[PDB]
Image (cartoon, rainbow over all chains, first blue to last red; front, side):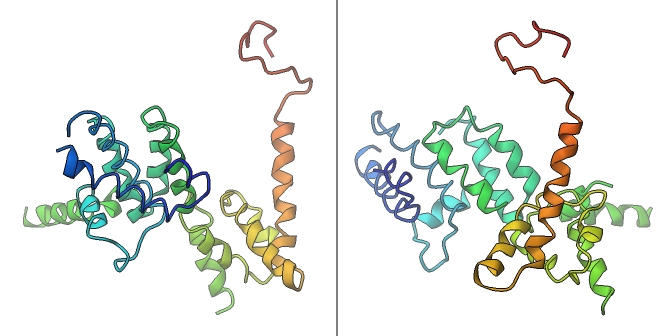
Length: 123
Length: 128
């Protein structure tokens, strides 16, 4: 259901369906297995949306507040995602260009679509 | 010479204390600081400043040594909205002249007789 709304260009309705996947695995998974791979896909793709559309503190939930303090899941890909939330808060045009070159094999091409639309809306 | 001191403020404050114990044409200069430069994130903000250059002279103040070519392509989008409603645009007329002159010289930098690109056997045809 998250692969539909990014074809349908519903990037704000796409934040509603990613916080519902993560609220069940802390009730059912804590992670196991089958539920351990559902939580890798949902904390790499809720970070590429809050820089795409950067919500105001009224409509920023207490679940969205927790994940952005940790940055400002594999050890290869956990290190390049703390570095990308910093640059768009510093508006660093040279920092964002060398990371898509070095995060293209890491993601899959559903997560490769959300990183393309951030680098344009900051440049 | 680099920008590293102005990026990290806390590192630069600690090393200075170590040693010592031991308006017409005024408007033209302010817009150069973000255009004759390497690259910025001011693009929607960079495009509006070039508009009220006095419009008799765009090419003298756009076609120069190093103007940001990422300030030339979003310059084309904002001068269209003026034309879609109303009067002809000094943003969009004089920046069609700048776009197509840089296109020719790179093809002038290209060789004469073109051979087809082949990613399977690239150097096998010739020393082209």
